[PDB]
Image: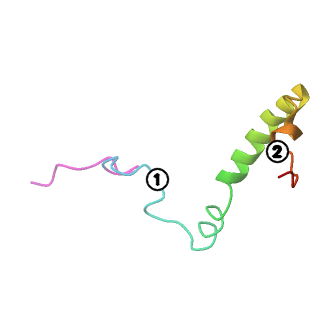
Amino acid sequence: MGDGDLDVELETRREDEIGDLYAAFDEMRQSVRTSLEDAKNAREDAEQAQKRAEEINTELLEHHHHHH
């Protein structure tokens, strides 16, 4: 009796301040609204900037025209 749990710095270590205990209904409503697709767009454009320099005849892979 009177013993079993302690470690009152944080207590039991079952939660490392992971954000499930406290957050805010404004930053979490805009941080997920756009960021992952913008990081994708930046990483993709920075690769495509090396590939556009090889030509590949890119415009002939579309060739928008009426030719029946």
Identify residue for label 1.
18
Question: Which mark identifies residue 31?
Answer: none
Q: Residue furthest bottom?
A: 25
Secondary structure found at label 2: loop
What is the magenta range? Answer: 1-11
Q: Residue furthest top?
A: 54
- Answer whether residue 66 is magenta in the image: no
Secondary structure found at label 1: loop
Q: Quadrant of residue 29?
A: bottom right
Quarter of the image with the N terminus is bottom left
Q: Residue at x 86, y 38 (%)?
A: 60
Q: Earlier in the sequence, mark 1 or mark 2?
A: 1
**Picture layout, residue 61 above or below residue 32:** above
Q: Main secondary structure of the magenta part?
A: loop
Q: Residue at x 71, y 47 (%)?
A: 39
Q: Is residue 68 left or right of residue 34?
A: right
Identify residue for label 2.
62
- Graded by Cα atoms within 10 Å as few (under 14), some (14 to 19) or many (20 or more), the crowding at tag 2 reads few
Q: Quadrant of residue 47?
A: top right
Q: Is residue 64 left or right of residue 32?
A: right
